[PDB]
Every structure is written in C-alpha cells, then in structure tokens.
Length: 223
Ligand SMILES: CC(=N)N1CCC(Oc2ccc3c4ccccc4n(Cc4ccc5ccc(C(=N)N)cc5c4)c3c2)CC1
Ligand SMILES: [Ca+2]
Ligand SMILES: [Ca+2]
Ligand SMILES: [K+]
Image (cartoon, rainbow, N blue to C red):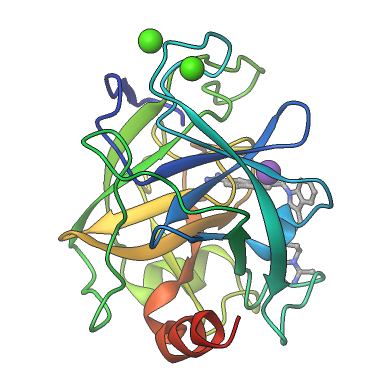
C-alpha cells in the first residue's frame, strides 16, 4: 500500500497473510475454514497467518494454519489476469475472535464512487521498494468503468474494476496481491494488478468479487 496509513493491530480482522517461508500475498477469511485470494498468488506449501499485525514479530494473537487444498478459478488466464481468484481451505478451522473475523460475500456489485478499504503488507513506495512490517490501510473509491478502460485499453474485462486515484499517490502495490477490497462491509475486490504503483492515470485493478459469489458458495459446499 502506497500513501496509506498504519491500520493498527487487528483493525482488519479478516486480513490474512499467505506465507511460504515468507509473506508473499494477502488474502481474506470468508469463514472458519476458507480464504479467498488471487489465482496469481497460487503456490504449493501455503501456510495461512491470521490475526497478524507485524509479520516479523509474534505478538501472540496469531494463528498459523496450513492449507489443505487450493482451488484456482477454472477460467483463470495467467496472461490477462481475467478471473484472478483462488480459494484456500484450512487444515483446521480458525478460531474467530475480535482479531480474527470473517468478511461477508457481497449480495450485489458496488457502484462507482463507493468508498473502499484496501489493506496489505505490500511495497509502500511509488517508485522504490520499501516493505512494511505492519499492515497498511487505504481508503479508495471505486472508479467508473470508463476511467478504468481508458487507462488500460483492451485489458479490462467485466471481471475487473478500478479503484484508486487518477491523480496517483495512493494505491495498492506488489506484496498486496490477493488482499481484500471491502466496500460497505462486503468483500468487493481482490488486489490483482496494475501499472507500477500510485502512478498518475494508472489506478489499481481488482478482481470483481460480486461476479464470483455462486462459484465461491458452490465450490466451498463441495470441498
Ligand atoms: C497481456 C495482458 N493482457 N496483461 C494484463 C494485465 C497483467 O498485468 C500483470 C500481470 C502479471 C504480473 C506479475 C506477475 C508476477 C510478478 C509481478 C507481476 N505484475 C506486476 C504487479 C503485480 C501486482 C500488482 C498489484 C497492484 C498494483 C497496483 N498499482 N495497485 C500493481 C501490481 C503490479 C504483473 C502485472 C498482465 C498483462
Ligand atoms: Ca504491532
Ligand atoms: Ca505478528
Ligand atoms: K504481487
């Protein structure tokens, strides 16, 4: 997150860190046994870390649970990032508390201009590299589809939306991938891609979750 603020210890309780010996992507807990992240974050040997603030210090609220199963969306296209979503099932159920909570699936898509909260442990530099230890937060509005498509000609699909600032300075970045985009208390997006980070006229692109609700519900019920 570029141009964000320090959220504060367990302020985004559904935020998950995917670890494979190091943090490599964010995720969102949708229930005691399932996490939603991006298909581009797919990897073997995933450990899910819940209730994390500072990823390099154990402050005692953490729950480290191995993944038993990974399911990348059937139509995921690594070339275009269309359908950038994966489900991750936990070996054992997480213990929900004030620090570890699940986020609800959206019942409908959100409108352009709706304010959202994006979070993660990604790079905080527009151009440079500086990874934080504590979770960063950022408020950003959903952009109009026209603005999104104008910004990335021939690359935006109906499964994507843009959020951020056209004037740049604030965005998600590498390290935030797979992370939640929460608008009006529902998971509306997943940090997917972009052109650099916080650049003028290059907002963040997010997987449009509301398109995936029956897929998520059905997949979960059968696994
Ligand atoms: C050909 C085509 N249709 N494309 C559509 C868009 C897609 O963009 C991509 C595709 C793949 C990768 C990729 C893979 C490994 C490591 C870093 C990679 N990056 C850079 C990358 C990755 C994640 C981001 C999250 C947020 C932001 C952001 N500004 N908020 C930028 C990111 C940049 C990519 C950007 C690939 C090109
Ligand atoms: Ca801390
Ligand atoms: Ca910690
Ligand atoms: K990334």
